[PDB]
Image: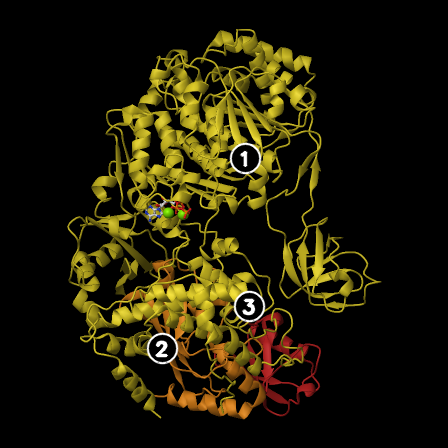
Chain colours: A yellow, B red, C orange
Amino acid sequence: TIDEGLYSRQLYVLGHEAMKQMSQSNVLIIGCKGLGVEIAKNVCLAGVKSVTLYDPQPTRIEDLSSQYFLTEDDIGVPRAKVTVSKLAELNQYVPVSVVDELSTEYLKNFKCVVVTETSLTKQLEINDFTHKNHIAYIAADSRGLFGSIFCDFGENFICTDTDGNEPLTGMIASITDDGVVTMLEETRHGLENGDFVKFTEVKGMPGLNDGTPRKVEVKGPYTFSIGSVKDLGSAGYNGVFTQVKVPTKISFKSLRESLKDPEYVYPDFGKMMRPPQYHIAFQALSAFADAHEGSLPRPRNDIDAAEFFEFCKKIASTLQFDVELDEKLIKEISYQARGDLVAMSAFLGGAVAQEVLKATTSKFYPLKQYFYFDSLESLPSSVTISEETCKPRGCRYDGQIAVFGSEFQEKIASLSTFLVGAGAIGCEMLKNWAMMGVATGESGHISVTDMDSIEKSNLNRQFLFRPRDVGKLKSECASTAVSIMNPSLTGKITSYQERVGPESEGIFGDEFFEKLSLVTNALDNVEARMYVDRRCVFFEKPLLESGTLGTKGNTQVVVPHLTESYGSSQDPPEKSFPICTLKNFPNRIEHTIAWARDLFEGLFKQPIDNVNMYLSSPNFLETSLKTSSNPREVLENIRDYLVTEKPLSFEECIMWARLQFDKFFNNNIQQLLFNFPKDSVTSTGQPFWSGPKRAPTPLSFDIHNREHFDFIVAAASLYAFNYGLKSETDPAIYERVLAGYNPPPFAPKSGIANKDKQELKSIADSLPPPSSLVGFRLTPAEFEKDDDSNHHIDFITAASNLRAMNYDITPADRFKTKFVAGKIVPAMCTSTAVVSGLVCLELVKLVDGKKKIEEYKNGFFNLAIGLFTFSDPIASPKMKVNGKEIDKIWDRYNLPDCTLQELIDYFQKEEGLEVTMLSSGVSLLYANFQPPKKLAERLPLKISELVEQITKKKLEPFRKHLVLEICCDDANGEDVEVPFICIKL
Amino acid sequence: MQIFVKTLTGKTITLEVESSDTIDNVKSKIQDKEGIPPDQQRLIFAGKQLEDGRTLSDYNIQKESTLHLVLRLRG
Amino acid sequence: ALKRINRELADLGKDPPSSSSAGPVGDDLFHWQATIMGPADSPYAGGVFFLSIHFPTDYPFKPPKVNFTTRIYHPNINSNGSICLDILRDQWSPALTISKVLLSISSLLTDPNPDDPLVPEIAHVYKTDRSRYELSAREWTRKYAIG
Ligand SMILES: Nc1ncnc2c1ncn2[C@@H]1O[C@H](COP(=O)(O)OP(=O)(O)OP(=O)(O)O)[C@@H](O)[C@H]1O
Ligand SMILES: [Mg+2]
Ligand SMILES: [Mg+2]
């Protein structure tokens, strides 16, 4: 009874069984500061059985530095009581409660226990009991720019899936008697030594088809070994190998035992000596807090730092840690002990939420065991950081001023950012900006633009939207929510509903872009990302790109004149199958799904478009006759959908659906088998239907079968929708009509002047004149995956399953069909939180105006295996032009609106280069091979007039510049790249 | 004897070979003359693709036969 | 994008293909009308075939859309002019050039591949009755590729 209308995107990451097992586990959360509330939000969105909170401390002002459910009217009230009311509205299936006091035995009521903002002694006391009762225990701590996570899931943890990937499967060419398994030509299995696989459909070696997993010895990228197959046979031909994923046993240690001899996880190999430092540092922090009634060292205080360093020395001596303590790092930890940043809190909350999901679902590889992280490179260097500047001012930004100071806070308050998109990443970025006080000053401003509307499936990871807000614009709702969270941002936020593209340049023009400070992308398509990147490059504004895919995520920062752009590197491609495979010989369910999608487009979309365009364009037939690739096909479609097969009731739609079923599933297969019989051989003598090619078999229509009836119903419903008729779903009418159907005979055909134009004309004139049919339009079927009442995914699933039955392929259910056909990108809330945290950690670097390139870090992470990596951005390539250093990306030529001849003369005389090609937009303004008449006609014209003449469209009033791409050759004719030209209108 | 190999660009290469010469030797001559690796040479005669390990006589290649040199593409 | 397109165009201009000529439509770089000459040692000898090339906005990250315009009787070419080649579907690296695309197309016309056909009936005729295939190809290249 999983609510598939809400967990649609998450179920593609976790699965049905994972969520079924997750919906029976209770989670307790001790500590309700920023990290605790973030973890609670993520867990509630995840869909656990219930959530319990425990934080009886009264609210204070500084606690609002990272809490977004607390207001200044809540000072003095326990955090849990004022937080549960707002947390209960995130998910309706996840009850949230509060416990005033905590007892040890009560801990047995929960499946996972998260501990934050707790002393080390209490953590040890809790762990000594939660370890021997097999309860997952996750302890998190966030001090300034440092974070620590500790996980303990018992001594007999069972991990079903250790990487989250699908089992590797592939085809086999030949298997020798020595266990040498060989793939097909230029086919790499991708297995690793120690993996287990099972073989099926192996010809000549039936023994390997039993299904028993066997060890794998990798011998090369194309072959491997399994051992000895002497008994089973001599040589095996063809077959499929499939990887088998086995459960693993992971054994942890208690907190008390792991304190002496911990097991670190290193997020970066450039700084390998730090985690040992953090292990001592956090224990010393706890000891100092215990020695000052829970009072952390004051910000940038020398005496407290010295005492903390003494405690660090004492602990290091006590534990016999053979590591030299770094005094500078320890004193920095002491200074920022009272820090409370929203970016670090969000990052650690996402990580801990993912760990909780791993613990509950027994999936993915967890942390083992300690994880110490720091972002000390984010510390501002352009402002004076001292005890005087970092002292609290009794405001809600004290937790951040205590790290960065008042001057950097004022710098943040005057930012002018631009957020593209208002999805989940946009919502997280807006929350972080609201917490940080971005654009709360006099000169600050925030602009957010997004044209999409809130849907039901977006509420799973977008916490700023509520079910009552379904169907409204994202930007307005987000702006209202974040203005409610921070009242100081009333009137400082502008929400647009415009798609960022070539058609929105009239609003987001030069005037708009000259006041921005940075651009943050929250998009989901590559074209818009690359357009925004081009715009940022033109205006030279810092850009923040972030992308997620399931549990993987990456963040990149583009800085003017320092790093290369984001469009300069386009790694991730897509896959489009060869047409011969899809059209005739499929061998996987994806092929059938693609074929079904193409069939849907060709049956319900293109013919309707042709019919509608015929009745609108007065000269449609003549244009199509000399423009369309297949005028004959268009004419046939128009005739069939207008006169030949125009339905007058739903029964005729059912008959048409049956006829199409027969056409596509019974006749084409017979034709193919007549052309290529099952006993046919290739040119080399090998059997034709062997290997990737599977012998098909025609299907006979059986009404009692579920799939045939589903296909008939879906096709009839779609046809009726196209013709605007009244559809029915009662099987009685279908069984009554389909009984009286006479299948037309069909026998395969072996085959064996300029009248074609005459035949096409005869077909054309048969069509009724457009004047005869006025106001008669057919409704095209626009594909919509999210709607479950239009029979789209049902029809696609039915067609794919029928085609799979044609080729004896394994059918897929509606869930996977919707995943594949709809191009749904898996998404998670934890990944969104992590990428938002990383982007906001880069944002403080950007604000400080750091100049070196080694101080920025593009980040990548995979939460399935707990992998985190950070690398320096790639510097923008340089070049030598006219004996000068030119940046390839961030340099341009600024010229007036001079004539083309004057531009050529300028490039010939100044740069000493000969212009050979000059283009703008999608037009070729000037080329060296054009006829001399055309050039002489175009030379004495200005650039603006030339563009207007070529593009046949006047320049709009808001346009103020032109971007020209110029390719020029040197004196010797050697091609040399030059930066683009920025013509100023 | 003599044979003619036509390339994809319209060029005609004349070779001095013997009916007993192996396909490997012909691919070697084509690599020596044009610099095309043997792995990428697809030699065709009378609608049949020449395979390594055999001789010209196996394909009934005689005086002034014409072969085709194309790239290894399949699909 | 535009820069790579013009670099390839200049390379075509400087290096004469001698059997093909690809050029943009009017002054649009995202639409070319190329020409291919029928191979001499093929039934399609003495024929001119026109191709339409639509460059995607993500070129060269995505393969160009190349579609035949002149009707041709080939086992691996359907009626709609669609072509059957890997370098257009998933073998499209950023290293390919229309130059080579055309080379490939020509090599295909030189020798068909009936083991993995796109038109099953023509492939069957070619495999069974070679003479009928030769006659049909000659008739088609005379009716469409000539004049
Ligand atoms: N060209 C564009 N201009 C403006 N906003 C855009 C553009 N393209 C995408 N977006 C916005 O980017 C966000 C993408 O986020 P996300 O993919 O999570 O949302 P969605 O597409 O609505 O959901 P789903 O992926 O679950 O179907 C959406 O807010 C969408 O409106
Ligand atoms: Mg949407
Ligand atoms: Mg989306």
Question: Do we see residue A356 in this rendering?
Answer: yes
Q: Is the same chain shared between marks 3 and 1? A: yes
**Mark 1 belongs to which amino acid?**
Gln
Q: Tell me if label 3 and label 2 are in contact, CB under 8 Å.
A: no
CA separation in Å, label 3 and label 2: 25 Å
Q: Residues within 10 Å of mark 2 (few under 14, many from 20)?
A: some
Viewed as shown, does residue A67 lie left or right of A316?
left
Residue at left 53%, top 9%?
Answer: A306
Q: Is the same chain shared between marks 2 and 1? A: yes
Of residues A189 and C104, the one nearer the viewer is A189
Q: Is residue A976 above or below residue A123?
A: below
Of residues A416 and A98, the one nearer the viewer is A98
Q: Is the same chain shared between marks 3 and 2? A: yes
| Subunit of label 3 | A
Q: Which residue is mark 1?
A: A354
Q: Is residue A565 above or below residue C98?
A: above
Mark 1 residue element: helix
**Mark 2 belongs to which amino acid?**
Glu
x and y percent of residue A495 in the render? 27, 38
x and y percent of residue A255 in the render? 66, 22
Q: Which residue is mark 2?
A: A633
Tell me where residue A932 sits by quadrant: bottom left
Q: Earlier in the sequence, mark 3 or mark 2?
A: 3
**Mark 3 belongs to which amino acid?**
Pro
Tell me where residue A365 sits by quadrant: top right
Q: Earlier in the sequence, mark 3 or mark 1?
A: 1
Of residues A744 and A589, the one nearer the viewer is A744
Of residues A330 and A229, the one nearer the viewer is A229
x and y percent of residue C83 in the render? 45, 73
